[PDB]
Length: 178
RNA sequence: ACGGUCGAACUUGACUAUCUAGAGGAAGUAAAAGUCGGGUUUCCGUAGGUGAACCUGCGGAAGGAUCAUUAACGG
Image 1: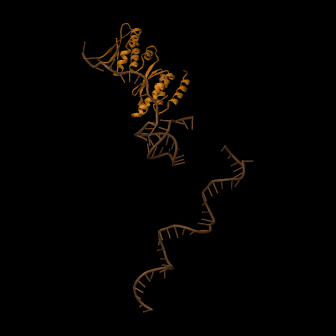
Image 2 (image 1 turned 180 degrees about the vertical axis):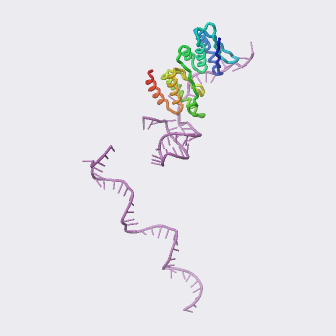
């Protein structure tokens, strides 16, 4: 029996505690994996028991809990539980353009937009989920959808206004046999 | 008449300033319906790319649209 341990930061302890039943129930019910949260090591531990139905379910659960810790909602990583062709690609915001200080903050703003609206628009077009950590961007979706979302985000964080980005991603989504 | 003094003005070169004729050159204008025919958020300073514009490099600005998380840490 093998196990996987994944860490949790201090800012994700309370979301883990509130959503704990919605996390451990799908892992143990139909995947059949033991789960605990070590408070000393601050780790979510997932284990294979005799009740595990099939191999690689523990990898599925590990991706689910890792996606929840990175900042995604519990149902958007339950999508990683159910679907097979889903991945979790992430990058830093300074990876494409060296931005210092206030400029960097403005880049973060034009991933969000007003009220988060711009971000949601990309999530509507690329069919992905984007999480903005403090200087990090995480995309959950299919491989081509991750490519479209990262193209939109990289276009946003090197200077393009949101309307041009919307038009470009709508043209690409029309061309992508969606 | 010698000499001294005040000194107009005259001649010669330089510095000039003004007035006044000009062969020629480079132009433009009116007359010829004569001949041939897509990219960009907005900038600043410096440098290069054929002068400017524009593009790129380097360093700066916003005069550019912040969503989500963050009470435990004791045995």
